[PDB]
Amino acid sequence: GLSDGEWQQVLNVWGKVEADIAGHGQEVLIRLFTGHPETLEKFDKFKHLKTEAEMKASEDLKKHGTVVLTALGGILKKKGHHEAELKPLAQSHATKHKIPIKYLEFISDAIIHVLHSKHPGDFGADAQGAMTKALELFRNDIAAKYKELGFQ
Ligand code: HEM
Image (cartoon, rainbow, N blue to C red; front, side, top):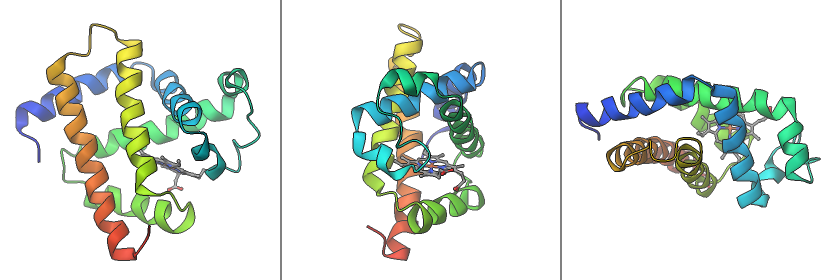
């Protein structure tokens, strides 16, 4: 649950992402894959990537980064009223991709890391607080659907 002022911070930060969605999406996935190499094994189309240089050179990884952040941005713009947008993603990630909630924690922290890396000194403590709360809400509502499905 976020206040109006917190949502305003989230959507202000998101403007930074929308200026370069592919570059942000690429770096988020690279941070996930290099920090948590077990996550790469869930992607049949990226498991061939052995080095970060190959990851950086992969145009399909940048494409998928655009898909991921476009979906997340659509959810964030609903300011919590995201049941219709979130349900299909919860279902596909639990039942088809088999993504444990832990990996959603990993990618949430990766987003925070990338924002500081690309905007050092321009991602203030209030903005980090609000973005963190928004990603916690996203993860918590996914977790509720995971529990319904019995997925661990
Ligand atoms: C912010 C969190 C995430 C968002 C918004 C997101 C979004 C998406 C979307 C929109 C798709 C394509 C449609 C679909 O299959 O539902 C997708 C596919 C997929 N996601 Fe995610 N995802 C997220 C996190 C993760 C994480 C953490 C993992 C694994 C560590 C993951 C694994 C996958 C896989 C394996 C696919 C299929 C890729 C393919 O072969 O095309 N997702 N995701």
